[PDB]
Image (tube, helix red, strand yellow):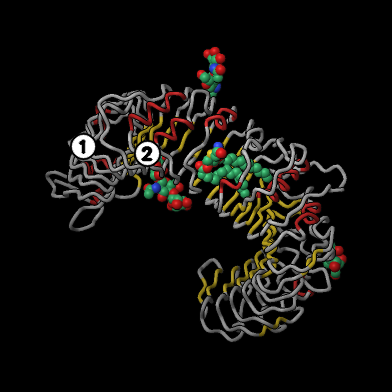
Amino acid sequence: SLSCDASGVCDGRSRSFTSIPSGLTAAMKSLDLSFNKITYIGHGDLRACANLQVLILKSSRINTIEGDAFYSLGSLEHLDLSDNHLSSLSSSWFGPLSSLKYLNLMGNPYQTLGVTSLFPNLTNLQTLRIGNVETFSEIRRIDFAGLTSLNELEIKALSLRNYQSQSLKSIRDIHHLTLHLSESAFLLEIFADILSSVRYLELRDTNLARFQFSPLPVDEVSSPMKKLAFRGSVLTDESFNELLKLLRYILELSEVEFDDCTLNGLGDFNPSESDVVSELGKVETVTIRRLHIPQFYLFYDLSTVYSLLEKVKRITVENSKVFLVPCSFSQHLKSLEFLDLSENLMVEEYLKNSACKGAWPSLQTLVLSQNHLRSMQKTGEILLTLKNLTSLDISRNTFHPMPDSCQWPEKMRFLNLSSTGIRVVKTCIPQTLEVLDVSNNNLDSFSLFLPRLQELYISRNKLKTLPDASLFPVLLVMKISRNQLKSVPDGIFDRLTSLQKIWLHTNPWDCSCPRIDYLSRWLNKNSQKEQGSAKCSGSGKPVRSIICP
Ligand SMILES: CCCCCCCCCCCCCCCC(=O)OC[C@H](CSC[C@H](N)CO)OC(=O)CCCCCCCCCCCCCCC
Ligand SMILES: *[C@@H]1O[C@H](CO)[C@@H](O[C@@H]2O[C@H](CO)[C@@H](O[C@H]3O[C@H](CO)[C@@H](O)[C@H](O)[C@@H]3O)[C@H](O)[C@H]2NC(C)=O)[C@H](O)[C@H]1NC(C)=O
Ligand SMILES: *[C@@H]1O[C@H](CO)[C@@H](O[C@@H]2O[C@H](CO)[C@@H](O)[C@H](O)[C@H]2NC(C)=O)[C@H](O)[C@H]1NC(C)=O
Ligand SMILES: *[C@H]1O[C@H](CO)[C@@H](O)[C@H](O)[C@H]1NC(C)=O
């Protein structure tokens, strides 16, 4: 009861099959039999479809597959066996799949990949996922024999009990290596085997409390590793310092991320300057999200971090409860062009210190999105200390009504006031602006003349009148959806002579014909420009559909 499209793509998904359907053809290119009750797959179940390029067998209850079940699938590029009941993999399965590009074996209860190298024959393999949560317990030297380059290899071994050294060393080039480890017992040697191949290493769920550095005795390897990411990791002030020492081998590391990690800190840890690292190679981007520091004052005078960021260009510390980025700390950030402290507890008085005189000398973009700032003027005033600043995001902050005059950094051309609760826009906003987002507020009208404005975002408001075209002589983009606009003055969009894109949907457009003429005739002559589609209130029919005599 499977249905195929004219292109040879058949759906069999969730159809209660207890066995592969009979009478398949060589016309099929993609066969999806996910979520079925297919316990056994015989020698001849898939013998016909010799031109199959995609086989989706995910989450079916497969626990038995004959060694040569896939003997005629020489054109198969995508095989998905994840989440089944395979507790033993057979090398005979992958033998005839020299055209295999994607192999997902994750989610099955096997304990190891088996006694025979399963992938030597897969010469065009680009993606491979293996392992599980409860039982995968051993990686061995024969496991990846025959694998030269993989764009991605995911290994889930949260229950790993033993890793044979050099197991991953045979692989020449791994673009993205995702490892799920519950502890750090084998992280070091693993790290010694991937220094030549891994460009992006992603560590998930690892408790690194007991990590300890030791000199990697692998021959001079110019690690091509550009990105390193930790997710849901447990760290300590001690183990953290241990990790830092690892950088000497990944001289090219440019991006580091820490997602949902907890940093446990204690006072008993206080080494001299010899133990600590203050050289951060080429690390130029630091992203930190949802970082939990149980007890922050249990950290000695944090000067240890001042020499690490001299060269950092981009930093993001979000939703990690930051209330202060100490002045001296900021002055050390000589190269910082981008700083994103979204979702923290920043307020004027502490911002003042964070953005002191020589704070962030080169900052161009500063994001203080969800914080506790309350005065627009006060914030612009405090930020005057920043001379290179060109972009500022202070959206999602609850501000008081803005004055008629304000002081903002001079080169500022981007100001985001989205979701800030304002009800009125005054001249506090500079004429120097190029991009302005006051979308999702409480505005009734926009009367600000900004001659250099190229983009205005004013969606999600209550404007009953479209802002006069002469206000933005050279506008390229206007976003005024989700408002209360019922109509537009004849010829107004033809007055936006640089307009390239415009959002008008979610507005109650009055489509009676005397009125809606120009607007409808305009949407027809400029469909390319309208993003999304404005409909008529009442019928819901697209405005452009209306024609008047
Ligand atoms: C593989 C190598 C990767 C290398 C990555 C580089 C990491 C550096 C990132 C720069 C952090 C920028 C924000 C610092 C703000 C600050 O100083 O928070 C301090 C404030 C109070 S100031 C404290 C006083 N001055 C002391 O008496 O706390 C606060 O305001 C709130 C506490 C915020 C705690 C989280 C952020 C603190 C930085 C964490 C650094 C270690 C990260 C380890 C992750 C596993
Ligand atoms: C001006 O500030 C706006 C508010 O901060 C901002 O809108 C926000 O845009 C981000 C873009 O990623 C959205 O991100 C969230 O949602 C995505 C998926 O949709 C998630 O993957 C992200 O992790 C995140 O949770 C926000 O949803 C959106 N905020 C809202 C509520 O509208 C504008 O983009 C800024 N304007 C300009 C011109 O930059
Ligand atoms: C970032 O801004 C600073 C401050 O304006 C710039 O450095 C100053 O450049 C002037 C040149 O007119 C020198 O006279 C000063 O000595 C510098 N001030 C400092 C920091 O001591 C810097 O050039 C800007 N960087 C960028 C983004 O180009
Ligand atoms: C798969 O092909 C044969 C087995 O018939 C053998 O050479 C080896 O297992 C694989 N090929 C390679 C790359 O050596």
| Mark sitting on residue 55 | none
The local crowd at label 1, few if under 14, some if 14 to 19, many if 20 or more residues have their Cα within 10 Å, is some
| Mark sitting on residue 373 | 2
- Residue for point 52% across, 23% down: 358
- Residue for point 80% across, 41% down: 222
Per the model, the C-alpha gap separating discs 2 and 1 is: 25 Å
In the picture of the structure, the residue carrying the numbered disc 1 is 445
* Residue 111, image x, y percentages: 74, 75
Q: Give the vertical position of 315 relative to 122 (above or below).
A: above
- Residue for point 52% across, 27% down: 359
Q: Disc 2, disc 1: CB below 8 Å?
A: no
Q: Is residue 132 visible?
A: yes
Q: Is residue 23 visible?
A: no
Q: What count of labels does the image hold?
A: 2
The local crowd at label 2, few if under 14, some if 14 to 19, many if 20 or more residues have their Cα within 10 Å, is many
* Residue 511, image x, y percentages: 17, 50
Place residue 368 in its image quadrant.
top left
Q: Residue furthest left?
A: 514
Q: Give the vertical position of 542 relative to 427 (above or below).
A: below
**In front of the other: 405 or 220:** 405
